[PDB]
Amino acid sequence: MEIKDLKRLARYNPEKMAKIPVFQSERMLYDLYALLPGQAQKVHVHEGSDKVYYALEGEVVVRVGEEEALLAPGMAAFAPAGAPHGVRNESASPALLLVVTAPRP
Amino acid sequence: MEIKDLKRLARYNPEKMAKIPVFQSERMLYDLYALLPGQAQKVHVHEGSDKVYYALEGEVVVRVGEEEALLAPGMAAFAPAGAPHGVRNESASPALLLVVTAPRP
Ligand SMILES: [Cl-]
Ligand code: NA
């Protein structure tokens, strides 16, 4: 079956953040976002999907709507469709997120 | 912004596995499954939804289709639509899973 150790899949790119697909689903994106310090997924609105950022490792500043919060390990932030959202690693350490998007964009 | 510390949401039902919705998304179920030893999510089939189990804490024996594997902490298992799936906490410790089902069944 498709069963993986998420952290072991994480690959950080010095040039820019990386999105590492965990599973290939026709109904969602179940990815890892590997952000080195200073890297980020720019804030954007995706009207066709809901996204949930879950911090697996490290921390990122997650923005949903007009709010930002520190998404520390173990925390999940919900970015429902229409809400501008993004994550930025402002820390001095890598940050790894489990990012789920439904439906598949 | 809806941001939650997943572990802090865990609650256990002694009579049966506790299903604790993390977020109410129209696009997916993003739930926590709190399984005390011996508890389980009986085998189920979502003809039109994919489900991904991610072991936040503890371990469960995850069944997806014709296979069963130990879903240890940090591991995620993918149950594509149609595949019978379930999780059983056969350990002597509680298990907490982040379970995503998309779309909502
Ligand atoms: Cl993909
Ligand atoms: Na069913």
Image (cartoon, coloured by chain):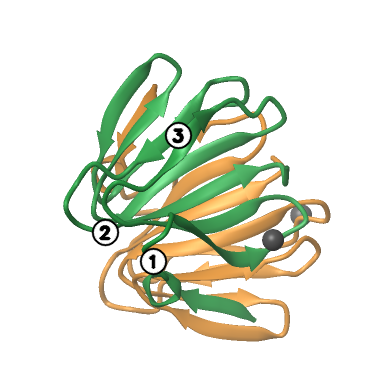
Chain colours: A green, B orange
User: What is the tally of numbered marks visible in this picture?
Assistant: 3
Q: Quadrant of ligand 2?
A: bottom right
Q: Amino acid at mark 2?
A: Pro
Q: Are marks 1 and 3 on the same chain?
A: yes
Please name the residue that numbered disc 2 is placed on.
Answer: A94
The local crowd at label 3, few if under 14, some if 14 to 19, many if 20 or more residues have their Cα within 10 Å, is many
Q: Amino acid at mark 3?
A: Gly
SS at mark 1?
loop
For the point 36% across and 48% down, which residue is it? A39
The local crowd at label 1, few if under 14, some if 14 to 19, many if 20 or more residues have their Cα within 10 Å, is some
Name the spot of residue B3 as percent of width and height, x first: 34, 31
SS at mark 2?
loop
SS at mark 3?
strand
Residue B55, relative to residue B25: is it above or below?
A: below
Give the alpha-carbon distance from disc 2 to disc 3, as whole Å: 16 Å
User: Upstream in the sequence, badge 1 or badge 2?
Assistant: 1
Name the spot of residue B9 as percent of width and height, x first: 30, 40
Q: Is residue A27 left or right of residue A90?
A: right
Please name the residue that numbered disc 1 is placed on.
Answer: A12
Name the spot of residue B51 as percent of width and height, x first: 64, 57
Quarter location, residue B56: bottom left
User: Upstream in the sequence, badge 1 or badge 3?
Assistant: 1
B26 or B14: nearer the viewer: B26
Asked if labels 3 and 2 touch by Cβ distance under 8 angstroms, the answer is no
Q: Chain of mark 2?
A: A
Q: Chain of mark 1?
A: A
Q: Nearer the viewer, mark 1 or mark 3?
A: 1
For the point 62% across and 66% down, which residue is it? A23
Please name the residue that numbered disc 3 is placed on.
Answer: A86
Residue B11 visible, this orientation: no
